[PDB]
Image (cartoon, rainbow, N blue to C red; front, side, top):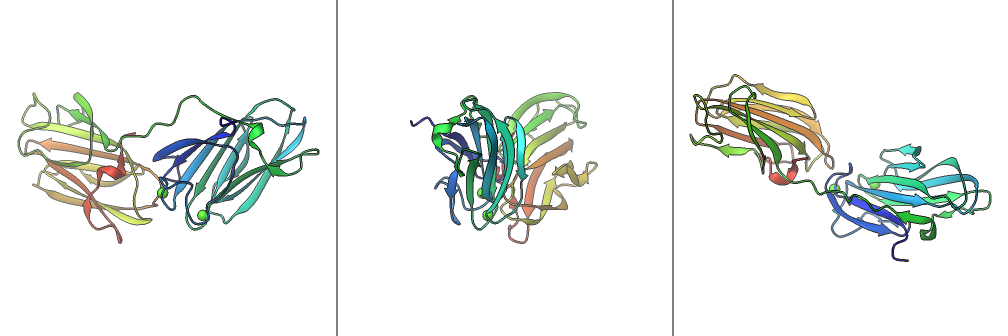
Length: 291
Ligand SMILES: [Ca+2]
Ligand SMILES: [Ca+2]
C-alpha cells in the first residue's frame, strides 16, 4: 500500500525553513550515519516533520519512544508527550498515553540534525504490543496543504516621503544592492525624498559573530533577530558606512528589517555582511527570504 505511512516534510535548515520535498515514509526508522536523507538535502542543519494519524491495535497504556540524533518533539492526540529539542547523540526518550483500539489519532514528530551523526526512529509498546518500530499498517499520512517554498529576496515597501508614511507600492527586491543614481525608485516625490522598508528572513553559512555593513546616501536602520544593530537615520554623507555585530548560528532563519531614507541626494543603499569565515560581500539573494 504505497499510501501507508506518515507524510515527511524535509527542510535544508534545522528550523523548518528551506523546504525541499515532501514524501510518504512508511515508517520512522532512519539511520543516515553522517549523511542526509536524500541527495537534495545538504550535510548538517536539516529538519523533518512527519504528520498523519496512528491507529493502535489495542485499548491500552501505550508507551511512545523516539531514538534521535539530534532533537525531537512528539505529539499524539495533540498532547506533547516528548519535548527534547536539543543537541544529542542517539538517545531514547519516551512517554505514555492511553489509546483506544482502532481509533485514528493525530501524530506529529518534529526532528532535526545539527552536525555529525543523524538518525530518527519512532517505536511503541503496551501490555499486548511488543516494543516495535511503529509499522506502516498503523500509520496514515496527512494530506491537506503542502508546505510552500518561500521566495528569495525581501518584501520591500516603498514610501513617497522620508518618514515611512505614504506607502506607494510593495514588491520583492532580490537583495539590498541599489545605486538609483538620480532616477528615484518612487515617482511623484517632493525634493527627491522617499524611504524603503525591507522585511524578511536571513540565514548564514557559519555559526559566529557576523558584521552587517551599510553603504548609503541617506539614513539607515538595520535590525537582525529583532536587535537594532545599525542606527544612522539622520545621515546625509554620500556612501556613508555603518556596521554592527551579532552572533548568529548557521542552519536557521533570523528576522531582518532594513529601513532607508533619502533626503534628496542621488539614492544608494547596499547591505553587506562579513565574518571570520565569510568574506565581505553584498548579502546574496539566496540567503534572504521574503516570508
Ligand atoms: Ca542545512
Ligand atoms: Ca547530529
